[PDB]
Length: 152
Length: 48
Image (tube, rainbow over the protein chains, first blue to last red):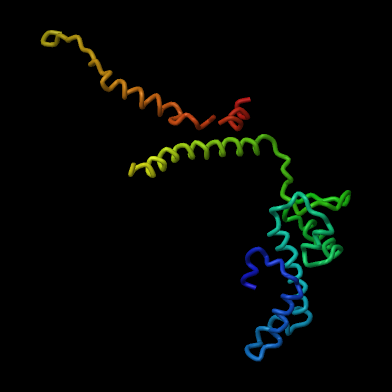
């Protein structure tokens, strides 16, 4: 679970179910399990909110390659079903702590960022800062090339 | 003015340095490398 604190470990949920159901199968310290999954009205609810965890934190982690993603292949890369993904979209999207944009006009929509509606600002940042990096290139090009030419 | 008559003054022929007194100045005071703004949007946004 500590490893889960990066990349979300978008793992087959049943595998983690093994990893945390064999806690109840501990021939050692098992009171951890009973505090976690020896419970029913909350321990099984802990499994449920763990599904919540995997889906919503995967929504978090996967925010990079977006602007093109399908409702079906969403579930395919979600370790959970499509209408399961439908309810997950629904709750995370009415919660809307992030701003995505989606529509079943195609179903190929995504847990997006503002979807880049911006003017030159994008171009501005890009051109300016990149060109600046290039002047930096030059200004250390002279330096380091001279340095490697010191002995000569 | 009694006890105080002024003398015509001047600066030296300083090209010996005036050269390096403008060469380094112009080269730096003007975008140094000069390959920098070549600010261009946010400036004209506020401008226009």
